[PDB]
Image (cartoon, rainbow, N blue to C red; front, side, top):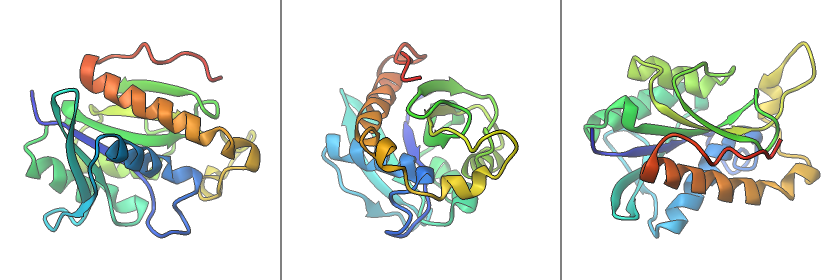
Length: 188
């Protein structure tokens, strides 16, 4: 299909930039840095975008600018704006169901309790869209991941986040360049 869109999820505000639920943004910024682009306001979607290309291929890096719950209300207009089909949309996000640091790639599947993802699946009218899942761990047997995703990483996890984002950024580039997975080694 063609035009490409990479969306990083997260909440706004400098106070949320470091939280576990903002890995998508961090990886987004990382990719914008890589590829030498800066984010600009997108009045058609309300979100901010960065444009450039990874190895010859046209990209559109975006970050929503609203609360996580409303991700789709901006993403949907964004995919519509650039004539971008779901199969070609790639959303980066923290995943409560994967071991901290473990990066797995897929199209379809569940949202893993991610409110930003439900919004996206709701807005695009499909679950078929590519995801760069980045494990953050999960509160222990029985519940409340919600508050957990709004916490910053522990100092221990903090020493690893930079490396995990570099790998998640590479995984994205690979997806775009070759598809499927084989970047899923075990950062168990």
